[PDB]
Amino acid sequence: MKSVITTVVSAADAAGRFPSNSDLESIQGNIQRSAARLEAAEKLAGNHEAVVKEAGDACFAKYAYLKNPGEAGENQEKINKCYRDVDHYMRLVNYCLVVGGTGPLDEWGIAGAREVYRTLNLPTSAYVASIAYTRDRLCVPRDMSAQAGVEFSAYLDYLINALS
Amino acid sequence: MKSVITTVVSAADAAGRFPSNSDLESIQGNIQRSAARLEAAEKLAGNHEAVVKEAGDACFAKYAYLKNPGEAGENQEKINKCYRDVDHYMRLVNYCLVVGGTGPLDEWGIAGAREVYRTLNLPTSAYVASIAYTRDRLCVPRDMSAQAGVEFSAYLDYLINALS
Amino acid sequence: MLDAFSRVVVNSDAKAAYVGGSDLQALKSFIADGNKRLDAVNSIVSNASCMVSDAVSGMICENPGLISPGGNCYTNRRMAACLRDGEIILRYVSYALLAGDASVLEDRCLNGLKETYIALGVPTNSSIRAVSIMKAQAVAFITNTATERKMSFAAGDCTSLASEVASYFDRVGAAIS
Amino acid sequence: MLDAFSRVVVNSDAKAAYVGGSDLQALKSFIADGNKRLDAVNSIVSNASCMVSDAVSGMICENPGLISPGGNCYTNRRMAACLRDGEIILRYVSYALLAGDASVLEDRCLNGLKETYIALGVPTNSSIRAVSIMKAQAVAFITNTATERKMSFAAGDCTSLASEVASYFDRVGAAIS
Amino acid sequence: MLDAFSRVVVNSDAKAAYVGGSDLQALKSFIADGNKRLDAVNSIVSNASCMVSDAVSGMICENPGLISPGGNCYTNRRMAACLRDGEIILRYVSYALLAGDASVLEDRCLNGLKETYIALGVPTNSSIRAVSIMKAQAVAFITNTATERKMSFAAGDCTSLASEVASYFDRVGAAIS
Amino acid sequence: MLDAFSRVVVNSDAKAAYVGGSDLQALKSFIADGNKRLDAVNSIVSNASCMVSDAVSGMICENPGLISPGGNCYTNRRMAACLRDGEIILRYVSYALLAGDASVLEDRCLNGLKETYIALGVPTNSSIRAVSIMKAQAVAFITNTATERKMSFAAGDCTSLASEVASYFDRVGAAIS
Amino acid sequence: QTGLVNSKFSARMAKKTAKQTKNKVDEYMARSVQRQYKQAAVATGVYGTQCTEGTVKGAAEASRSAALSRQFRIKQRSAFSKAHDLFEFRKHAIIAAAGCSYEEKMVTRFPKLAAAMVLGQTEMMRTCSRYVVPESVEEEYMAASVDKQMKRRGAPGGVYSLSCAEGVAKGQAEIARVSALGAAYRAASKSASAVTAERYNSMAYGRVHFAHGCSYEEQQFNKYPAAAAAMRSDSYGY
Amino acid sequence: ALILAQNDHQEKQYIKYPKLAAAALMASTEVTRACQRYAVPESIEEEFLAASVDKVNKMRGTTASGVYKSSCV
Ligand SMILES: *C(=C)C1=C(C)[C@@H](Cc2[nH]c(/C=C3N=C(/C=C4\NC(=O)[C@H](C)[C@H]4CC)C(C)=C\3CCC(=O)O)c(CCC(=O)O)c2C)NC1=O
Ligand SMILES: *[C@@H](C)C1=C(C)C(=O)N[C@H]1Cc1[nH]c(/C=C2\N=C(C[C@H]3NC(=O)C(CC)=C3C)C(C)=C2CCC(=O)O)c(CCC(=O)O)c1C
Ligand SMILES: *[C@@H](C)[C@H]1/C(=C/C2=NC(=C\c3[nH]c(C[C@H]4NC(=O)C(C=C)=C4C)c(C)c3CCC(=O)O)/C(CCC(=O)O)=C2C)NC(=O)[C@@H]1C
Ligand SMILES: *[C@H](C)[C@H]1/C(=C/C2=NC(=C\c3[nH]c(C[C@H]4NC(=O)C(C=C)=C4C)c(C)c3CCC(=O)O)/C(CCC(=O)O)=C2C)NC(=O)[C@@H]1C
Ligand SMILES: *[C@H](C)[C@H]1/C(=C/C2=NC(=C\c3[nH]c(C[C@H]4NC(=O)C(C=C)=C4C)c(C)c3CCC(=O)O)/C(CCC(=O)O)=C2C)NC(=O)[C@@H]1C
Ligand SMILES: *[C@H](C)[C@H]1/C(=C/C2=NC(=C\c3[nH]c(C[C@H]4NC(=O)C(C=C)=C4C)c(C)c3CCC(=O)O)/C(CCC(=O)O)=C2C)NC(=O)[C@@H]1C
Ligand SMILES: *[C@H](C)[C@H]1/C(=C/C2=NC(=C\c3[nH]c(C[C@H]4NC(=O)C(C=C)=C4C)c(C)c3CCC(=O)O)/C(CCC(=O)O)=C2C)NC(=O)[C@@H]1C
Ligand SMILES: C=CC1=C(C)[C@@H](Cc2[nH]c(/C=C3N=C(/C=C4\NC(=O)[C@H](C)[C@H]4CC)C(C)=C\3CCC(=O)O)c(CCC(=O)O)c2C)NC1=O
Ligand SMILES: C=CC1=C(C)[C@@H](Cc2[nH]c(/C=C3N=C(/C=C4\NC(=O)[C@H](C)[C@H]4CC)C(C)=C\3CCC(=O)O)c(CCC(=O)O)c2C)NC1=O
Ligand SMILES: C=CC1=C(C)[C@@H](Cc2[nH]c(/C=C3N=C(/C=C4\NC(=O)[C@H](C)[C@H]4CC)C(C)=C\3CCC(=O)O)c(CCC(=O)O)c2C)NC1=O
Ligand SMILES: C=CC1=C(C)[C@@H](Cc2[nH]c(/C=C3N=C(/C=C4\NC(=O)[C@H](C)[C@H]4CC)C(C)=C\3CCC(=O)O)c(CCC(=O)O)c2C)NC1=O
Ligand SMILES: C=CC1=C(C)[C@@H](Cc2[nH]c(/C=C3N=C(/C=C4\NC(=O)[C@H](C)[C@H]4CC)C(C)=C\3CCC(=O)O)c(CCC(=O)O)c2C)NC1=O
Ligand SMILES: C=CC1=C(C)[C@@H](Cc2[nH]c(/C=C3N=C(/C=C4\NC(=O)[C@H](C)[C@H]4CC)C(C)=C\3CCC(=O)O)c(CCC(=O)O)c2C)NC1=O
Ligand SMILES: C=CC1=C(C)[C@@H](Cc2[nH]c(/C=C3N=C(/C=C4\NC(=O)[C@H](C)[C@H]4CC)C(C)=C\3CCC(=O)O)c(CCC(=O)O)c2C)NC1=O
C-alpha cells in the first residue's frame, strides 16, 4: 500500500537512515486531515447499498446499448456481476479513506485493469460514467462535511484519471 | 536536501507518478509544527553569539588538554578557529529549524566530517561534548516554548548520533 | 531538489548568516496560506489526465501538420510518446507548484530537453502551444473559472498562486524555445 | 508490506466487508495516541548510538567467547558487522513503531535470517541475549525510566507503547536462535 | 571538384595506373551521348522557375499545416526562405547532371545539410516531399512526358539520363533525413 | 529582442488570434503604471557606476580568495574585467526593466554565459554573490530604502516593479549557475 | 578564407570546442567512478574472485575485444535510442545516489557519468544477473521468468537490435558462452559470507529501483532476490 | 562608419574623407576579431550557416552578368 506512513519508511530505508523530523512531521498530517478523511469513511460504509443501485443504472442510462446481445449487459447475472464491480470500487474508495493514501485502489483495482478490460471486451468508458456520477451528485453540506466532500471527491477522480 | 516536501516529491518521482492525496497530506504536517520550530529559529538567530561563548569553553571545560603543545589546538588562533567551527554547526541546525528536515546537515555537516577530523587530528569524541552540553542546557519555558524544545533537542542529539 | 523553504537557506548560505526574523516573513506569510497551495494543486491533479487530452488535441486542431503522413504525430507510437510527455511536464509543474520553487524543473525535466527535441526533430514551435494551453488550463482550474467543472473551495483570492503556475509553464516555454 | 492503518483494510478485505463503526474504535483511538506515538519515536532516534553499544558490549560482559580466537568478535571486520546489524534491527523496530505494525520485520529482517546465520557460523545463543538486553533499554527510553539519561516530555501513561515494542523484540529473537 | 571525366582519374590514381582504352569505354560512350545530356539539362533549366513553384505549392496542398501557425513555412519570410532553397536544390542537381557525377552535390550543397535542418527545426519529413516532387518533375522533362507542356526534341531513347537524375535526387533525400 | 508589448503579440501569433479585450488588460495597466517604471529605471541608471563598485568590493571582502596570487581578481588586467562584466549585467538588466520583458537580457548576455565562465575559470559561487548584491541594491533603490541616499519620488507603491527587477537578477543567477 | 562548403581543400576548425571538452570531462569521471567502484571489489591488495577475465589464454584477450566492440554499439545507437538512453540513466542514478543533492547535481550535467555509476553500483553491491546463482529450481524459474521479459526489448518489434548482440566476428560467440559459464560457477563457488550479502542487497535493490511502494513486487523480491538481481534498466536492450 | 562613430566629430571626419572610413572599418574588425579570417565555427551546423552567406558574398564578387570581377582574384 502507498500511504503517508508507507512512503516515509521507504524513503528512510532507501537512505539507510532512522526516521528523522522530516519523516516524523509527515504523520502530523495524519492528525488534522484524518479527522476529515475519516468523516467520510462511515458515510460510505453505512450507505454502501444506496450508492451502488442508483449509480449503477446511471452506467446503463448513459450506455443503454449493452442490452443488445453480444455485449456485456445482455443477461441479468451479467448485470448482477456488473453491480458487484462498482460495489468493489466504492469499497476500495472507502479503503483508501481509512488508509490515508491511494494504496488499496492501486494495489487491487487499477493495476492490471487495463489488460483485463481490453481482452474481455469491457468498455472502461462505461466504467467511468458510474464513477463520475457519484462525484457531481455529491452535495457538499448534505452528504458529508465540507472538507470531507473535497476529500472524497479527490479520491474519486483519481480513479477517473486512472481509467483515462 | 531532505525536507518534508523534498522526500515526498522525490518519492513520487521514483515511479513517475502525480502528487497523490497522500502527498498533499504530508505537506499539511509541515504547517502546524512548522511554527513550533520557526519561533526557535530567530530566537536562536537573535542569541547565537552568546551560545558559542558558552559552547566554546565547554569543550575546554572537560578537555583542558587541547592547549597543550603537540596537539591541534595549541595556539590562540586555533581556539578562535574552534569558536568559528561550532558556529557553523549552530548555523546548520538553524537551517533545519526552517526546512524541517536534516537537509543542510547530512551534506554540509556530516558528509566528509568523519575523514577531515581523522586526517587533521581533531577528536570527534571530544567534539561532541560541545553540542551535547547545549542539549541539557535547555530551559523549556525560559529559552523558548515547550514544543520547540522537543525538536531542537532532537536535532542536536541527531548530530551526536551522526558523528558517533 | 530544493523548495521555497530551502531557497532562502541557500541564499543565506552564500552570506553565511543566520536567517533571523526579518527575512522569514516571506515564509511566515507562506505557511499562512499553506492550505491555499494544497487547495490549488488539488485542482490540477484531479484533472491531470484530462488536461493533456485537452492540450494535445488542441495542438492538433490548431496545427494540423503533425498528423500529416511523415509528421511528428502520425505514427501511433509517436502520439503515445507525445501524450507520455504531456503528463511528465504536468507532473513537474505540479511538483514545482507544490514545493513553491521551480528548482525541480530545470534539473529533472528542462535540463537537456531543448537539445533533445532538436535532435529528435520535434517541432518546438507547436510544442510551446501544447504547454501554453496547459498554462491557460491551470490558471482556469486554480481560480475556478473553468467552464465545464467547478469545485468546492472556501472563498478568497488566489491570483498570487494563479501567477505561480503561469510563471512555471513559461519557464518550460522559455527553456525549450 | 502492511502497517496499522492497512491492517484493518486487509482484515476487512479478508471477508470483503467495509470499514464501519465496528473496526474504527482501534483507529479513532490511534490518532489520539499519535502524539504519544510521535513522541515515542523521537525518544528512540535521539540515542541509538550508545544503545547498540549498550547491547553489543553487554553481550561481551556476559559472553567473552567471541573475543576468544575463533569467535565472532575476534576480527575488527566482524565487530563492525555486529555493530552495523545491531542498529539495523533497531532501525526496523523504529520503523515498526512508526508503522504501528511489525510488517517490515518478517520480510526485511526475519525471513532469510535463519538461513543466513547457519551459513556464517553465527552463535545462536548470542542472538537472544543481545535483543532482550536492549529490549529493556528500549522501554527505558519509552517510559523515561533510563537511569543515566533523562528527557523532557508531556505527562501521561505510556506502557501501551512500551508493550507494543515488547511484542516486537520476541518475534525476531525467536526464529534465529 | 570531381566530374565524370575526373571521377575515373582519381580511381586510377588510387593505384597509379595509366588510364587506358579498357577504361575509356565508359567515357567514349559518355561523350557520344553528350548531345543528349545537353538536350537533357536544357529541359530542366528552361522550366526551372515554375518547377520549384510546382513542388513547394505541391508540398503545401498535400500538408496544409506548414502554413498553419507553428508550421515552418508559415510566415511570408519563411515561404520566401523555402522557395529560395527550393531552387538551390534544383540548381545543384543541374550542376551534377551537367558534370555527370554527384560530387558537386554531396559537398557544395549537402556537406552539413543534415545538422543544419536539425538545428534550425526544419522538418525532415516534408523536405523529402519538397524534393520528391522535383524528382518526378525531372523524369517527366527528361523523357518529355510532361502532361501540360511538351518540348520539341530529336527522336531517340533517353531513359538513362532519367535514371541518373533520379539517382541524384535520392542522394538529396538520403542525406537530409 | 522583444519587449512587453511584443510578448503578448507573439503569444497571440501562435494561436493567430487578434489582440482582444482580455489580453489587453495586462498592457493598458502597463501604460498607467509605466510612468512609475521610468521613475524606476532612472533611480537605477543614475547610481550605475557606484552600484557595480559596491558589489565587487562586497565580493572581495566576503570572498578574499579572489585577490590571492593567481586568483581570479588578482591583477588589474583581471579586476578591470570584473568591473566590466559587473556593469554589462547592470546595463542589460536596466534594458530588461525598461522594456518590461526579460527577452533582451537572455539572448545578448545570458545565452552562452554559463559555458563562457566555465571556459575562463570564473568562479560561479562568487559571481552568484556578486549579482545578488546588485539584486539587493536595485530592490533598495526602487522602493527608496537605500540607507545612505534617498531620492525624490511621488508617493505611492512600487513593489510590483521591485519584484520584477528581483525576477531579473536571478535570471542572471539561474544562467551562470 | 571562406568555409569548406565552397572551393577549399582541407578540413578546418580543428580546435577543442565546448562539446569536445564536455565529452572530455565526462570521460574522466567515467575513469573515476569505475576506479571507485572497483575499490570495493579489490579492497585488499589481492584481486578478488570476480575481477577475472577468463580461463583460456585466448579468452582473456577476447573479453576486451568483445567489450571494445560492445562500447561501439552504444555509440552506434539511433537518435531516439540515444535520447531514451540519456534520460533513463538520469532517472536510475538519482535512485542510486539517493540522499545527496550534490551527488544528484553532478549526474544531471555529465551524461556518460550516468552510464558509469548505474553499471558500477549494480556491480558494487553485486545485484547483477551474472553474480547470482539461485539455490533451487523454485528460485530459478522465478529468475528465468523475469529476464525473458528483460530480453523482450532485445527484439522490440520481433526484429533484433544491436545491443543484445554478442557475436561480432567469425567464431566470436563461443567465447561468450564459456566466459559466462565460468562466471556462473565462480558465483556458485563464491564465499558463504558474500552470497548472503548478495541476496540482501539485491532484494534492497529491487524494492527501491522497480517496486516503488508496491506490496506485491516487494513480496516476490523478498521471496526471490535472484529475480530481483535479474531486473535491470530498460535502456539495456538485452 | 557612421553607425560605429561615437561622437559627431568622428562622424564628420568619416564623411569628408572616404578613404579614412574604409580603414576605420579595418580598424574595428581587427581590434575585435570579427573577420572571416578569425571566424571559427564551433560546430558543423554553424559552419554551414557561415557558408550560407559566403555564397551571397561571392555573388558580389562577380558582376550581374556572370563575369568574374577584379575585386576577387
Ligand atoms: C480545437 C481546435 C480545440 C480544442 C480541442 C479545444 C481545446 C482547448 N480548451 C481550452 C480551454 C480549456 N480546456 C480545458 C480542458 C478540459 N475541459 C474540462 O473541463 C476537462 C477537464 C478538460 C477536457 C477533458 C479547460 C478546463 C479550459 C478552460 C475553460 C473551461 O472552463 O473549460 C483551450 C485554450 C484556449 C485558449 O488558449 O485561449 C484549448 C485550445 N479548443 C479548441 O479550440
Ligand atoms: C539477445 C540478448 C539474445 C536473445 C533474446 C537470445 O535468445 N540469444 C541472444 C542473441 C542470440 N544469439 C544467438 C546465437 C548464439 N548465442 C550464443 C550465446 C550463448 N553462449 C553463451 O556462452 C551464453 C551465455 C550463457 C549464451 C546466451 C552462441 C554461442 C550462439 C551460436 C553462435 C554460433 O554458433 O555461431 C541467437 C540465435 C540465432 C542463431 O542464428 O542461432 C540469438 C537470438
Ligand atoms: C484558490 C486556489 C481557490 C481557493 C483556495 C482556498 N482554500 C482555502 C482553505 C482550505 N483548503 C483546504 C484543503 C487543503 N488542505 C489540505 O490539507 C489538503 C489535502 C491534504 C487540501 C486540499 C483546507 C483544510 C482549508 C482551510 C479551511 C477548511 O478547513 O476548509 C481558503 C481559505 C483560506 C484558509 O483558511 O486557508 C482559500 C481562499 N478558494 C478560492 O476561492 C479559489 C478558487
Ligand atoms: C510516552 C512514550 C512518553 C510520552 C508521550 C507523550 N507525548 C505526548 C504529547 C505530544 N508530543 C508531541 C510532539 C510530537 N508530535 C508531533 O507531531 C511531532 C513532530 C512533528 C512530535 C515530536 C506533541 C505535539 C504532543 C501533544 C501535546 C503538545 O502539544 O505538546 C503526551 C500527551 C498525551 C497526548 O498528547 O496525547 C504523552 C503521554 N510522554 C512521556 O512522558 C513518555 C516519556
Ligand atoms: C508531444 C506533446 C510532443 C512530442 C513528443 C515526442 N516525444 C518523443 C520522445 C521523447 N519525449 C521525451 C520527453 C519526456 N520523457 C522524459 O523522460 C522526460 C524527462 C525526464 C521528458 C520531458 C524524451 C526524453 C524522448 C526521447 C525518449 C523516447 O523516445 O521515449 C517522441 C518520439 C519521437 C520518435 O519516436 O522518433 C515524440 C513524438 N512531439 C510532438 O509532436 C509534440 C510537440
Ligand atoms: C522550404 C521548402 C523548406 C524550409 C526552408 C527554410 N530554410 C530556411 C533557412 C535556410 N535554408 C537553407 C537552405 C539552402 N540555402 C543555402 O544557402 C544552402 C547551401 C549553400 C542551402 C541548402 C540554409 C542553409 C538556411 C539557413 C541560412 C538562411 O537563413 O538562409 C528557413 C528560415 C527559417 C527561419 O527564418 O527561422 C526556411 C523556412 N523550411 C521548411 O519548412 C521547408 C521544408
Ligand atoms: C567579475 C564580476 C567576475 C570575473 C570577470 C572576468 N571576466 C573576464 C573575461 C570576460 N568576461 C566576460 C563577460 C562580459 N563581457 C562581455 O563583453 C559580455 C557580453 C556582451 C559579458 C557578459 C567575457 C565575454 C570575457 C572574455 C573577454 C575578455 O577577454 O575580457 C576576466 C578575464 C579572465 C582573464 O584575464 O584571465 C575576468 C577576471 N571573474 C571573476 O572572478 C568575477 C566573479
Ligand atoms: C517474476 C516476477 C515478476 C514481478 C515482480 C513483476 C515485476 C514487473 N512488472 C513489470 C511491469 C509493470 N509493473 C507495474 C507495477 C505495478 N502494477 C500495479 O498494478 C501496481 C501499482 C504496481 C506493483 C506494485 C506496472 C504498472 C507495469 C507496466 C508498465 C511497466 O512496464 O512498468 C515488468 C515488465 C514486464 C511485465 O510487464 O511483466 C516486470 C518484470 N513481473 C514479474 O514477472
Ligand atoms: C457517501 C456519500 C453520500 C451521499 C451521496 C448521500 C446519499 C444519497 N442521497 C441521495 C438523495 C438526494 N440527494 C439530494 C441532494 C441533492 N440533489 C440535488 O439535486 C442537489 C444538487 C443536491 C443538494 C446539494 C436530494 C435532494 C436527494 C433526494 C432526491 C434523490 O436524489 O432521490 C442519493 C441518491 C438517491 C437515493 O438513493 O436516495 C444518495 C446515494 N449521503 C451520503 O453520505
Ligand atoms: C559487561 C559490561 C557492561 C556494560 C557496558 C553495561 C551495559 C548495559 N547497560 C544496561 C542498561 C541500559 N543501558 C542503557 C544505555 C545507555 N544508558 C544511558 O543513559 C545512555 C543514554 C546510554 C549509553 C550511550 C540504558 C538506557 C539502560 C537502562 C537503564 C538506564 O540507564 O536508566 C544493561 C542491562 C542491565 C540488565 O538488565 O542486567 C547492560 C548489560 N553493563 C554491563 O554490565
Ligand atoms: C495542391 C497542389 C498541387 C500541385 C502544385 C501539384 C504538384 C504536383 N505536380 C505533379 C506533376 C508535374 N508537375 C509539373 C510541373 C509543371 N508543370 C508544367 O507544365 C509546368 C512546366 C510546371 C509548373 C511551372 C510537371 C511537368 C509534372 C509532370 C506531369 C505533367 O504536368 O505533364 C505531381 C505528381 C502527379 C500529379 O498528381 O499531378 C504533383 C503532386 N499537384 C497538386 O495536387
Ligand atoms: C567587506 C566589504 C563590504 C562592503 C563595501 C559593503 C558593501 C555592501 N553594501 C550592500 C548594500 C547596499 N550597497 C549599496 C551601494 C551603495 N550605496 C550607495 O548609496 C551608493 C550608490 C553605493 C556605494 C557607492 C546600497 C544602496 C545598499 C542597500 C542599502 C542602503 O545602502 O541603503 C551589500 C549587500 C548587503 C550585505 O551583504 O551586507 C554589500 C555586500 N558591505 C560589506 O560587507
Ligand atoms: C564522479 C562523481 C562522483 C560522485 C557523485 C560520488 C558518488 C559516490 N559516492 C560514493 C561513496 C560515498 N558517498 C558518500 C556520500 C553520501 N552518502 C551519504 O549518506 C550522504 C547522503 C551523501 C553525501 C551527499 C559517502 C558517505 C560514501 C562512503 C560510504 C558510502 O558509500 O555510503 C561512491 C562509491 C565509492 C565508495 O565506495 O567510496 C560513489 C560512486 N563519487 C564520485 O566519484
Ligand atoms: C564495479 C566493479 C566492476 C567489476 C569487477 C567489473 C565486472 C566485470 N564485468 C565484466 C563484463 C560485463 N559486465 C556487464 C554488466 C552487466 N551484465 C549484466 O547482465 C547486467 C545488466 C550488468 C551488471 C551485472 C556486461 C554487459 C559485460 C560484458 C559481457 C559479459 O561478459 O557479461 C567482466 C568480464 C568477465 C565477464 O563477465 O565475462 C568483469 C570482471 N566491472 C565493474 O564495473
Image (spheres, coloured by chain):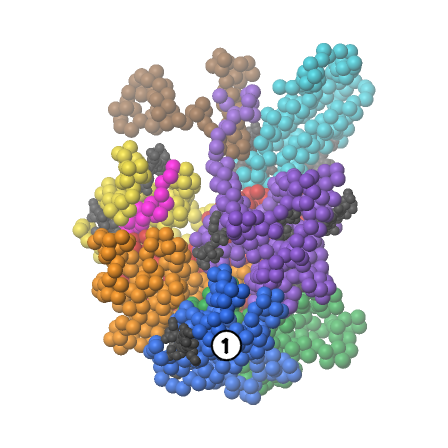
Chain colours: A green, B orange, C red, D blue, E cyan, F yellow, G purple, H brown
Q: Secondary structure at mark 1?
A: helix
Image spot of residue G39 (x, y percent): 52, 50
Residue at position x 48%, y 67% in the image: D67
Left or right: E37, with A133 as reference point: right
Q: Is residue C157 visible?
A: no
Looking at this view, is B36 or E79 the one in front?
A: B36
Image-quarter location of ligand 6? top right
Left or right: B69, with E174 as reference point: left
For mark 1, what is the residue? D129
Q: Is residue G167 above or below residue C43?
A: above
* Mark 1 nearby-residue class (10 Å; few <14, some 14–19, many ≥20): some
Image spot of residue C67 (x, y percent): 64, 49
The three-letter code of the residue at mark 1 reads Arg
Residue at position x 27%, y 77% in the image: B141
Q: Which residues are magenta?
A: F120-143
Residue found at the far bottom of this picture: D22
Residue at position x 56%, y 69% in the image: D122
Looking at this view, is A88 or G84 the one in front?
A: G84
Indicate the chain on which mark 1 is placed.
D
Residue B80 painted magenta: no
Image spot of residue H40 (x, y percent): 47, 29
Left or right: B61, with F112 as reference point: left
Residue G148 placement: quadrant = bottom right
Image spot of residue F153 (x, y percent): 21, 52
Residue C54 placement: quadrant = bottom right
Looking at this view, is G212 or C94 the one in front?
A: G212
Residue F140 painted magenta: yes
Residue found at the far right of this picture: E156
Left or right: G83, with F147 as reference point: right
